[PDB]
Amino acid sequence: PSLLKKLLLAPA
Amino acid sequence: RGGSPESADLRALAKHLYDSYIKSFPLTKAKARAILTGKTTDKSPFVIYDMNSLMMGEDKIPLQEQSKEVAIRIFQGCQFRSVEAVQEITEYAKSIPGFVNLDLNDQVTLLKYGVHEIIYTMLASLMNKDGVLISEGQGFMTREFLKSLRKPFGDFMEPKFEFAVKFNALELDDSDLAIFIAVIILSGDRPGLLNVKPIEDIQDNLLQALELQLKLNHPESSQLFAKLLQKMTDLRQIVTEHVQLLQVIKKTETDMSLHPLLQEIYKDL
Ligand SMILES: CN(CCOc1ccc(C[C@@H]2SC(=O)NC2=O)cc1)c1ccccn1
Image (cartoon, rainbow over all chains, first blue to last red; front, side, top):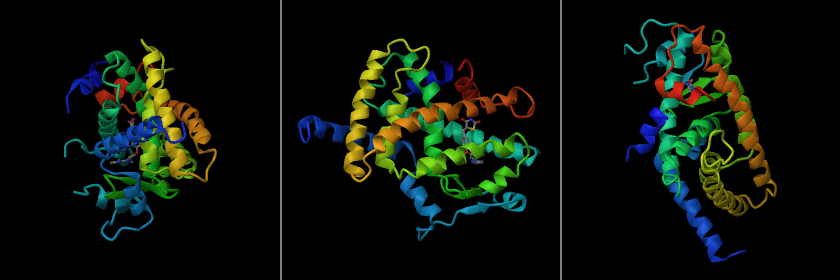
């Protein structure tokens, strides 16, 4: 999940 | 059910999705079709129809490019646009009610599978039979010129063009596409999902919002919804080509080096 996870977590 | 509060709520969902879509995706279909058919008063896209015009338009507005051959330089740009796309789709997905409250790994999985089908879907907005709009409508690359590119690059887009031609015939607008796109992301049958039932629950709600949207927005096309559900399977089938063509960077294309994010979306799929 690494990079997609990171995108999914970033409030934005 | 006809005109009940539940149907009013399905419209509210539709409008919410459409607003999130406006916000997630800078160039919309309405804006893309205006350029494609030469309706705008103010637009002027740069046309790339051959190698020379490519030399000219390449720098629309550094050491990313290096001294690489044209077909590779082009697909380096294709890789970036598609990373922008994945990021916008991810943001859009997060605006779908219920999405952020799903298990995070299921979110991942849904995006991992959904993102390619959504790229195909949204790319059609940017395509006619002649070429595709790029760099938010600032450029147009002809189908013919992309075919002229050396193997395997010269036939990447061609399948995307064929899908677009048939999907565009359905004449969906951006408000129809917002719901359709959401339906695709909340697919309860992706491999590896942990909790399938809460995903199917959001989708069923979305499918109903979709059905109502198409009756209200496309009153003369009684089978539209049935046709859309069919394009959903089509999409699953077309995207495997795409997935495989990006594994060509295993080798050959020893000078490709795939973007880290695209690598993640491709492997174990
Ligand atoms: C020709 N173009 C866009 C081509 O149109 C696309 C076709 C396929 C994709 C999917 C991506 S490409 C990849 O590597 N993996 C993906 O998911 C994304 C875009 C260019 C070229 C240069 C600059 C901007 N635009």
